Length: 383
Ligand SMILES: *[C@@H]1O[C@H](CO)[C@@H](O[C@@H]2O[C@H](CO)[C@@H](O)[C@H](O)[C@H]2NC(C)=O)[C@H](O)[C@H]1NC(C)=O
Image (cartoon, rainbow, N blue to C red; front, side):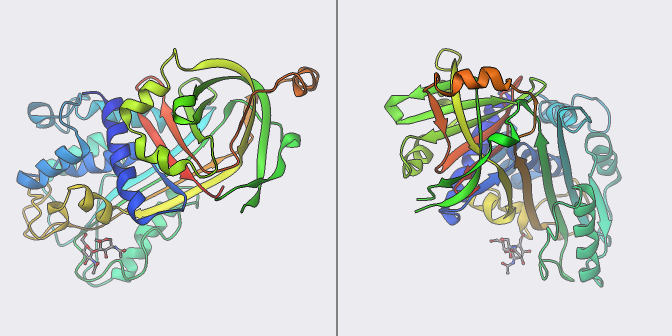
């Protein structure tokens, strides 16, 4: 009924599926971006193709989604508003963070695109739809696609489509890549970062940032875990770090978490501002997933098969999504707007005893504060 609710439910559904084939590895994706890519496809899907997407991504009760409203694509700044409003806001230039989104549908050129659709994507989406020749120059097409994604992500997301992933039979490809970097409200000082061991299960040294400051923390003895909120500068986004008490307690947490639990654990009465010592590793997160495998296991299957019904995009028989890929990159480091002086810090050094030390596997979420929507979610087992 709200983007906050829908993005979190969708996020945890995706998490449940990635857990299957990604045990003991880092996991990192952008739920909001995946929903936007699927919303774009949803615009031209019909029959069961459309129903499966709506059911799995839950566009159902969302503002801007639904029968009458969507029929107005091309005009009306209301279509898919609940999603577009967040993406439109976070992709704008600003002085505290950078969020680059490269999302696009590449369709074989031989497929005549329905003109009402082009207008549709043209007005609601940037990347949109782009014609291309897979038929006789597949390796050439793959180069074109990967070079667009690379160029659009500051040279960060490279070779998104693997060789042999595209051939003379490819109908349409969905690429959805995102890069995020944000400044903390409260910076960590470079001089305070030290090599510290991270107990992966055994351990390895990692660059561990450190600072003492006032932060919202939730302590849940009942679940043997703590949650720390670190605000990004600007007051529009924050990062939640869910840290189990024991080095090997992640599995339990991952089994119990969902939208309801996350909401309860972070409510204003459970969260409390406390002077605390924070240890957080510098992290360079980057993962890429085959969305076809993920979404199919989640319940979206027709759109990827000859039985797909995208008669809203074209009229040609056989238009289906032949490959769909998601890649997300984000660096977590010291950069911030303000810092405590060496004098106050000195006083805290031996007076503050409470600490939040993320030196073992944890879960983390970057959220949009106003909507409560999930922008990124991940599991960090190796910083
Ligand atoms: C991604 O996962 C899918 C399903 O597990 C793999 O299967 C492909 O499915 C697409 C439909 O979107 C077909 O067009 C391909 O011909 C299928 N390829 C095969 C033989 O598996 C798909 O291969 C995976 N993508 C890659 C290259 O990793």
